[PDB]
Image (cartoon, coloured by chain):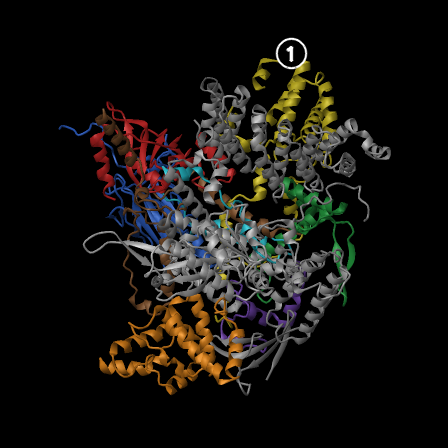
């Protein structure tokens, strides 16, 4: 369904490109709005910021697969490159639906220590992330543990 | 942005708000020669659970008023009948611990009718709540005026907000929407009905905005409430301190 | 001359500001601060900063004894707005608070309870730069909270600052320690909460922090305790500080 | 990986022959896309398709 | 009543905007090339042929007092898409035109030889730039500011009458 | 003198309307961008197989909101999507601010996404 | 009547539609091969995931449960999500009719949930309702997909 | 050029909104001042450069009452006031015929001695 | 390409800190780095040794080669340069994957 | 007579290049999602009092 | 409505639908009733990307005979009583019927049913003009050849 | 020529336009490393008025496969005068293209049979100036103190003929400008008898 869809979307790009080179219009943004997240690679990679250096990147497929032999830890996405392809999946609706299947946010938070904090609501809850200051106390004065 | 007073509305035991401004209602008319005429139109008792958003709209037909006088204190004795008839029909898992009345005048007639239920507390608000402006909601106004019988209607005033906000947050959105329909009804309705592509679902009371479209509109209702305080009292907002500004926005 | 385009170029900015402090000797402080209340709450950041410079230099000349109760109310409210909107590490808003609060000292007393709860709120915020300014404003206000005799308010701030000594961000952590130094050198050491024999052992591993703002603030607070309350730590604990 | 594909080019030419590898690659001025022939007579010319 | 206002705006282009847009030292040059302008060598590479099957183009200068001594100069016409024909006396001038003629009756900017790509087909044209003394193709006067299609062997003169023509310009196509 | 104040107050009110823009006196600028959504309905117009037969080219001049002549060819871009008038050369004159403006706008929108998507627990 | 091959981890079986006795409708995991000059569907391609790459996925789950950092509960969950996403977004349709891989996916999601339960020293199911594992990380959960 | 310096500092602060800009003060003003012009450029020549950023509805070149030659500055009004922000911060410091022009926002005051000049201007721009 | 290995890593040994310092030097003075690459492609014919380690995959083990960091900058340039030129000049035909 | 500025073969709307196209490609390796769950994370200010516009509307 | 929230069609909703119809004849009836609700009421609501998923959903169930060809009886091609969004539904439903069946098999089934609103052979020559013009725009002129005879006789 | 299947991606000729557009936009658009290469110089900060410093008067096709040549002498001969050549490739933090012109005795290769002592002295001066300008801190610090002592025995003519022209090139960096202004100031203090043509050049 991706491949049938990108057959359609790239042929629709090619006609609107000819309609606008013919008539000296500019393409309005709404002509390519519905197809922005379709395609293989993606419509949206036509307009990314570093597209002019990425035209010089050649043989990027075989480069990514030969990192087995030179890197000890590699990503499991050896087969796609989102600079050249765009991101080829979207999972935000899983996150909404798994909340709904657990019973809602009120049912989830009755399990927790939310009420002992004293906060009134939970839409602005933020967990501390990794900052780069965890081992910013020592330099080499650091044991094996 | 939020009042520090009403955090105890949202504990786990059931509460219920009761408001009675719209019970006995009158439109001015003129006689066909020309005069002042006072006809009674239909009225409603407003009853809200602030946790769940359940709205028990008790419609009051004009047929009850046609045979009496001194109606302005007969009205409050009818409200205490219907609220107490409402409490008895609920099973005791669902009966409220508290009824909160928006007016001081309702404490004595409700405590007369609630003698059968001694554990239930009846107490007034230190808040001032704009529940009288709920007749400016279109779906609610149509049902009261199409009514030919005394009848109860359940509504859901929170639509579907509860999926993604807490009831603390929905009660704050509600009483800002109801406060701005009270201060200036017609310009408040322009803000809600500005975009035609944003539609109200048939079983919903409000247009289905996105979560960023609600943040924009909530900022516009606060600017309506302040801009009309400045017209009414001839004050610039620059002369007001920040603590006075949140006092105006929250009543 | 008090427009957004004047505030954007620095050489016109410093000339319009000097003319305002020159003219305010004739015009008075009450006439001048009333004119600066609108640039102190403007949406543009560097126009808001230009007003904080003019406010600090006017109050340092003339005092605040001219101001009535309503301008003191409006002035303090505007400074709080310009503190709440700050997004860069410019220091004049703290020089501005210190100048106004030293001027009107005991008249500052009804304003102390809302500013402290604002400081306590910002210490819960997720941006580190917001947490850091909150503990900078705490350290500025400490001698005015003492002068208004509010010793229950100083011990509330000191127990809450003590609970934040586990902070990972060094620029926030250093200004927490500075404010605990400022409270401690004001207070009576027996009345202090938490007691010094709890505070000093918590400071001793923080001496191994490698960042300079944590270090120079912690040596001062260890050295203040070694002057004022040395018998509250055992001798083998003072030698671990020497090493 | 550059060496590896040029080294594997040799084995393709030993498996196909000069004649059939020219059919699949197209003329050098106007080459074929992947699995594209100039005609069907060229396609059916050889049992390797 | 004699004049409304003595001041009276112009609403007419002075030279400076067209001078800065269309570049040459000092004097603004007319003839912006149209969008289908191509050099012959860029037309041969797009069709991809070796030089034995490429078509060349050249403008050989034959003197009118004698064609017998041979070429005056030989100008190869493949490297560019347009060539300005103009006045290069050689005795102090400033260089304007690519193809310079030592003719006093010719302007600095007299005519251009313009290559175009009309539906995949290269076609050499020529335009009179509304010069002082006019231009004649095949000893026929030409109307100004339209591209007249050239063919092989044709002769360009830089003056309207046969009195002032001292050189010839032969367009040769293989 | 109350006569004289009104004659001056009209003079302030006359110079106020004379210095004020014609788009701004008439109507809000939100609507013409919303009229671009009315053409977004006309993307459904091209899909319809019946529209093939009604469609003919009846070429309309691009025209300002007050109704004034505009430029013909495709123009360089600005932050407000204002279109050039018919007296323009076609020569692009700039100190290059508008390109430098669009670069910060892209940069802000990019940086909002990466602040979430580069986080690690 | 079958032409079988295996490429890039996919097992492909091709039936022409003229050779099958009864043409029946299929789920996802079977392709419709279309004849280009007519646009008609003339063959069917059936898809599975190769046995060699079923074992590669199981060895990936064994590697996750042995790495440094696999005692930290959200780190283990995050590695479960990267390898599960990288499996499902690569094969997508071939997973459907590949039954030994579904059995291995059940065992792995149990083993990673057992790493959390054993790191808290208890296996009672009343202490670990599914909200502890499947609530998103922005609400304080593990966020296992 | 001081205007081009304050736009760089505004852009680095990430302001980018017109209502938070220093341009916001002049939201009622549709006229612009154009200065440091070359002496040969004329009214129809000014409408050509400045039409890139919108539609100019009035123009006034100021030129002496005796000799009738250009003082070196002009005024121009746009149909849309946002074209004023465009011209001010995008055409400022642009070298046109040797000299770099200066553009600023302005309040224009028309005079009596240039009255019939204003219709000799208006009949050109009423055509379009 | 060489930099993206370090996008994740928290604790680096001395060889990884030495590796990032050379890349940051190549950003800061790109013309002197580019002349170092040409000097090596013309003259350098003896090289430092390569370390090998094995990866655990439970069904097989697989070797990983770690090349010297200063030599990797030249090899990474030459990798990008050779695939860019083969693609322009159409060395590899359409069937090669 | 003015030599026009050279324009590309296809002109585009401005919004193609200010949108931040393919910006989610610069992620952490273990990021599942593209945006935050709540809008309250991504916004800085819920509401800011603009004394300029509110005073214009009153007066 | 769950299926139109996807970006593309999928075999999941079509395979699930067929299992319900071949279970019991009341599920057969709910699918015949829903096809008329989608065409007569709900057509105005749907965007063009949602009409690709609908016409391929219904054209897949029509071509494997879980719906009769006589469910297309409700469709009438008319200048006045054909929605622009309704005509987009027929194009997407018939492109799916051509791909599955093939064009020669599709002419067998359109002959076997008696659906007049698609192929009018009885009169009203402006409607016979509309239908031939409809189907050649879709890519189906071979279907039109019976109606092409009736028009040249009348003119 | 028939496709044998369909198109599912960007078509073939349409990718090549997009690769040709980046070729055309490549000279106009500034690269990130091209950005750093300019920013190192003092000239990048300057106004046009400030850049007036440098104005100041200081006084037939044949096609077919052929293999590349067996010894690519040409290729080595072209790049051996840009990289290797002859210099101290261990004490300098960098060597620039403009450094080829000014110093140029160190870059040259005439090892013996120089021109009687005095030009042995002329090379050591350009050795001192290269180590001051480009050298690391140990090399700079000694040759700075050596040049201060050897200045009185060198001619003032010899130093300012070589030192002053470096201060006029457009490639110069901020620390490189400072160190040569510093060398002038240490040289001027000792000699004290300065002629009228050299006062003008300073």
Q: Chain of mark 1?
A: L
- x%, y% of residue B23? 39, 57
- x%, y% of residue L158? 66, 20
Q: Using the rendered view, name the quadrant where residue I35 is placed.
A: top right
Q: Is G128 displayed left or right of H115 in the figure? A: right
Chain I image colour: green
Of residues I18 and C233, the one nearer the viewer is C233
Chain E image colour: blue
- x%, y% of residue E137? 27, 49
Of residues E65 and C139, the one nearer the viewer is C139
Chain F image colour: brown
Q: Is residue H66 above or below residue E52?
A: above
Provide the letter of the chain coloured purple: D
Provide the letter of the chain coloured cyan: J
Q: Is residue C27 above or below residue L10?
A: above
Q: Is residue F113 above or below residue H107?
A: below
Provide the letter of the chain coloured red: H
Q: Is A40 displayed left or right of H46 in the figure? A: right
Query: To which residue does mark 1 refer?
Result: L193
Instruction: Note whether residue H89 is visible.
Output: no
Q: Is C214 displayed left or right of L63 in the figure? A: right
Residue at the image position 40 percent from the left and 62 percent from the top: B59
Q: Is residue K95 above or below residue G133?
A: below
Q: Is L36 displayed left or right of B27 in the figure? A: right
Residue at the image position 70 percent from the left and 63 percent from the top: G128
Provide the letter of the chain coloured orange: K
Q: Secondary structure at mark 1?
A: loop
Chain L image colour: yellow
Q: Using the rendered view, name the quadrant where residue H107 is placed.
A: top left
């Amino acid at each position: 369904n991706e491949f049938l869809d990108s057959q359609r979307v790239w042929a629709e790009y090619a006609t609107k490109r000819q309609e606008a080179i013919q008539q000296n219009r500019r393409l309005a943004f709404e002509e390519l709005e519905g197809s922005w997240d379709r395609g293989i690679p993606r419509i949206s990679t036509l307009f990314q910021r570093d597209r002019h250096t990425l035209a010089y990147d050649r043989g990027h497929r075989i480069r990514r697969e030969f990192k087995q032999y030179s890197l000890e830890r590699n990503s499991p996405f050896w087969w796609t490159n989102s600079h050249h392809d765009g991101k080829l999946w979207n999972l935000n609706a899983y996150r909404t639906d798994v909340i709904q299947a657990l019973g809602g946010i009120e049912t989830i938070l009755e399990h927790t220590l939310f009420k002992g904090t004293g906060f009134n609501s939970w839409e602005g809850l933020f967990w501390e992330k990794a900052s780069g200051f965890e081992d910013s106390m020592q330099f080499k004065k650091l044991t094996h543990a | 942005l939020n009042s520090s007073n009403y955090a105890e509305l949202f504990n786990n035991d059931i509460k219920l708000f009761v408001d009675d401004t719209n019970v006995y209602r009158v439109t001015v008319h003129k006689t066909f020669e020309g005069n002042v005429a006072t006809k009674a139109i239909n009225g409603c008792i407003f009853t809200l659970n602030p946790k769940t958003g359940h709205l028990f709209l008790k419609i009051i037909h004009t047929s009850v008023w046609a045979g009496q006088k001194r109606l302005s204190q007969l009205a409050k004795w009818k409200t205490a009948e219907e609220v107490s008839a409402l409490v008895r029909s609920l099973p005791k898992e669902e009966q409220p611990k508290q009824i909160i009345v928006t007016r001081k005048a309702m404490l004595d007639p409700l405590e007369v009718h609630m003698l059968d239920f001694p554990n239930i507390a009846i107490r007034p608000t230190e808040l001032r709540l704009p529940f009288s402006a709920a007749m400016s909601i279109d779906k609610l106004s149509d049902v009261v005026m199409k009514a030919t019988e005394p009848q109860m209607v359940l509504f859901n005033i929170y639509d579907d907000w509860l999926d993604r906000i807490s009831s603390y947050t929905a009660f704050s959105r509600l009483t800002l929407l109801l406060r701005a329909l009270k201060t200036n009804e017609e310009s408040a309705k322009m803000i809600l009905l500005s975009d035609p592509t944003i539609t109200i679902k048939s079983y919903h009371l409000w247009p289905s905005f996105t979560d960023e479209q609600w943040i924009t509109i909530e900022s516009q209702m606060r600017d309506l409430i302040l801009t009309e305080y400045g017209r009414k009292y001839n004050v610039n907002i620059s002369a007001l301190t920040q603590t006075e500004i949140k006092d105006i926005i929250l009543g | 001359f008090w427009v957004r385009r004047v505030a954007l170029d620095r050489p016109l900015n410093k000339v319009v500001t000097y003319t305002t402090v020159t003219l305010a000797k004739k015009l008075g402080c009450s006439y001048t601060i009333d004119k600066l209340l609108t640039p102190l709450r403007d949406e543009a950041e560097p126009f808001r900063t230009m007003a904080v410079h003019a406010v600090t230099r006017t109050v340092n000349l003339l005092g605040t004894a001219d101001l009535d109760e309503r301008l003191e109310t409006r002035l303090i409210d505007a400074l709080l707005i310009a503190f709440q909107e700050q997004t860069n590490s410019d220091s004049i808003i703290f020089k501005g608070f210190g100048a106004v609060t030293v001027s009107l000292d005991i008249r500052m007393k009804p304003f102390l309870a809302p500013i402290v709860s604002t400081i306590l709120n910002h210490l819960k915020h997720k941006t580190p730069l917001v947490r850091q300014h909150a503990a900078d404003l705490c350290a500025i206000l400490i001698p005015v909270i003492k002068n208004c005799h509010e010793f229950e308010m100083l011990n509330k701030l000191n127990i809450i600052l003590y609970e934040s000594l586990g902070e990972v961000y060094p620029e926030v952590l250093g200004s927490i320690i500075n404010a605990m130094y400022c409270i401690t050198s004001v207070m009576d050491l027996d009345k202090l909460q938490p007691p010094i024999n709890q505070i000093l052992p918590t400071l001793t591993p923080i001496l191994r922090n490698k960042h300079r703002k944590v270090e120079v603030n912690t040596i001062k607070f260890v050295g203040l305790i070694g002057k004022l309350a040395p018998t509250y730590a055992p001798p083998k604990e003072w030698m671990r500080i020497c090493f | 990986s550059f060496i590896f594909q040029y080294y594997g080019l040799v084995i393709d030419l030993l498996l196909l022959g000069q004649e059939r590898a020219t059919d699949l690659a197209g003329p050098a001025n106007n080459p074929n896309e992947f699995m594209q022939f100039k005609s069907k007579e060229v396609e059916k010319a050889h049992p390797i398709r | 009543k004699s004049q409304y206002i003595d001041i009276m705006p112009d609403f007419s282009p002075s030279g400076l905007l067209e001078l800065e847009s269309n570049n040459k030292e000092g004097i603004a040059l007319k003839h912006v090339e149209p969008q289908d302008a191509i050099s012959p060598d860029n037309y041969m590479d797009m069709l991809g042929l070796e030089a034995r099957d490429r078509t060349m183009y050249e403008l050989v200068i034959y003197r009118k007092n004698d064609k017998d001594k041979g070429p005056w100069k030989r100008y190869d016409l493949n490297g560019r898409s347009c060539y300005l024909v103009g006045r290069e006396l050689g005795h102090t001038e400033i260089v304007v035109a690519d193809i310079g003629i030592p003719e006093e009756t010719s302007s600095k900017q007299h005519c251009v030889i313009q290559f175009r790509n009309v539906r995949g087909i290269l076609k050499c044209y020529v335009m009179d730039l509304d010069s002082s003394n006019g231009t004649c193709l095949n000893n026929v006067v030409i109307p100004g500011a339209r591209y007249i299609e050239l063919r092989s062997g044709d002769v360009l003169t830089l003056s309207e009458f046969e009195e002032d023509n001292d050189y010839e310009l032969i367009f040769m196509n293989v | 003198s109350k006569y004289e104040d009104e004659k001056a107050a009209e003079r302030e009110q006359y110079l106020k309307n004379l210095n004020m823009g014609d788009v701004q006196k008439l109507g809000i600028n939100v609507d013409a961008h919303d009229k671009k959504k009315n053409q977004t309905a006309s993307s459904l117009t091209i899909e319809d197989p019946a529209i093939t037969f009604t469609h003919d080219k009846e070429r309309t001049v691009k025209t300002s909101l007050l109704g004034r002549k505009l430029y013909d060819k495709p123009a360089p871009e600005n932050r407000f999507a204002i279109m050039p008038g018919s007296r323009w050369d076609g020569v692009h004159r700039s100190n290059g601010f508008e390109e430098k403006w669009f670069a910060k706008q892209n940069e802000i929108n990019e940086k909002k996404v990466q602040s979430y998507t580069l986080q690690e627990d | 009547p079958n032409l079988l091959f295996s490429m890039c981890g996919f097992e492909v079986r091709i039936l022409p539609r003229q050779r099958m006795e009864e043409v029946v409708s299929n789920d996802e995991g079977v392709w419709d091969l279309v004849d280009e000059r007519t646009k008609q569907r003339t063959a069917k391609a059936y898809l599975k995931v190769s046995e060699e790459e079923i074992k590669k996925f199981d060895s990936r789950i064994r590697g996750i449960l042995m790495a440094s950092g696999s005692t930290t509960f959200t780190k283990v969950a995050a590695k479960w999500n990267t390898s599960l996403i990288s499996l499902f977004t690569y094969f997508r349709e071939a997973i459907v009719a590949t039954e030994p891989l579904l059995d291995i996916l059940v065992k792995g999601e149990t083993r990673i949930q057992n790493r959390v339960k054993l790191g808290l020293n208890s296996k009672m199911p009343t202490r670990f309702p599914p909200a502890v594992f499947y609530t998103p990380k922005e609400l304080g959960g593990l966020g296992m997909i | 050029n001081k205007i081009q310096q304050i736009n760089d500092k505004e852009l680095q602060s990430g302001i980018l909104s017109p209502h938070q800009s220093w341009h916001n003060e002049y939201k009622d003003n549709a006229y612009i001042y154009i200065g440091n012009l070359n002496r040969e450029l004329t009214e129809g020549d000014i409408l050509t450069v400045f039409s890139e950023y919108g539609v100019p509805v009035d123009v006034i070149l100021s030129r002496d009452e005796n000799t009738g030659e250009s003082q070196g500055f002009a005024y121009l009004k746009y149909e849309d006031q946002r074209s004023t922000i465009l011209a001010v911060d995008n055409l400022n410091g642009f070298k046109i015929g040797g000299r770099a022009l200066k553009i600023d926002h302005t309040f224009y005051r028309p005079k009596r001695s240039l009255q019939k000049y204003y219709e000799a201007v208006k009949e050109e721009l009423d055509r379009d | 390409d060489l930099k993206d290995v370090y996008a994740s890593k928290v604790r680096l040994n001395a060889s990884e800190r030495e590796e990032l310092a050379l890349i940051e030097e190549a950003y800061d003075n790109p013309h002197d780095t580019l002349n170092r690459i040409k000097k090596y492609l013309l003259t350098q014919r003896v090289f430092k040794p390569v370390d090998i380690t094995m990866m655990e995959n439970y069904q097989n083990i697989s070797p990983v080669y770690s090349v010297d960091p200063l030599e990797k900058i030249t090899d990474a340039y030459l990798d990008q340069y050779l695939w860019y030129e083969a693609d322009q000049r159409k060395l590899f035909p359409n069937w090669i994957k | 007579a003015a030599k026009r500025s050279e324009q590309p073969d296809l002109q585009y709307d401005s919004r193609f290049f200010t949108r931040g196209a393919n910006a989610s490609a610069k992620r952490h390796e273990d990021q599942v999602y593209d945006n935050p769950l709540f809008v309250q994370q991504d916004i800085e200010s819920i509401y800011k009092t603009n004394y300029e516009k509110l005073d214009e509307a009153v007066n | 409505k769950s299926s139109l929230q996807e970006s593309t069609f999928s075999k999941f909703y079509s395979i699930l639908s067929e299992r319900m119809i071949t279970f019991h004849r009341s599920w057969q009836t709910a699918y015949n009733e829903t096809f008329e609700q989608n065409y007569t009421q709900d057509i105005e609501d749907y965007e063009t990307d949602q009409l690709r998923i609908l016409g391929k959903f219904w054209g897949h169930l029509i071509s494997y005979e879980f719906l009769p060809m006589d469910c297309l009886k409700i469709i009438k091609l008319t200048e006045e009583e054909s929605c622009p969004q309704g005509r987009i539904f027929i194009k997407f439903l018939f492109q799916e019927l051509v791909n599955e069946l093939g064009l020669d098999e599709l002419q067998l089934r359109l002959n076997s049913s008696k659906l007049d609103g698609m192929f009018p052979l009885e009169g009203d020559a402006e409607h016979i003009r509309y239908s031939i013009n409809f189907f050649t725009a879709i890519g189906l002129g071979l279907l039109t050849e019976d109606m092409r005879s009736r028009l040249t006789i009348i003119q | 020529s028939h496709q044998l299947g369909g198109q599912y991606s960007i078509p073939q000729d349409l990718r090549e336009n997009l690769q040709k557009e980046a070729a055309r936009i490549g000279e106009n658009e500034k690269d990130v490393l091209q950005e750093k290469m300019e920013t190192r110089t003092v000239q990048n900060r300057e106004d046009s008025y400030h850049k007036r410093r440098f104005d100041m008067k200081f006084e037939w096709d044949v096609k077919g496969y052929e293999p590349p040549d067996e010894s690519s002498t040409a290729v080595k001969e072209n790049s051996d005068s840009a990289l290797v050549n002859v210099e101290g490739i261990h004490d300098l933090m960098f060597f620039k293209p403009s450094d080829h012109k000014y110093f140029a005795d160190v870059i040259s290769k005439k090892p013996i049979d120089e021109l009687n002592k005095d030009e042995k002295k002329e090379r050591t001066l350009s050795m001192l100036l290269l180590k001051i300008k480009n050298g690391n801190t140990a090399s700079r610090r000694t040759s700075m103190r050596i040049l201060t002592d050897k200045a009185v025995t060198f001619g003032p003519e010899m130093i300012f003929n070589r030192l002053l022209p470096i201060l006029l090139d457009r490639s110069l960096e901020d620390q490189e400008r400072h160190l040569m202004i510093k060398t002038i100031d240490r040289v001027l203090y000792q000699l004290g008898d300065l002629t009228k043509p050299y006062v003008h050049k300073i």
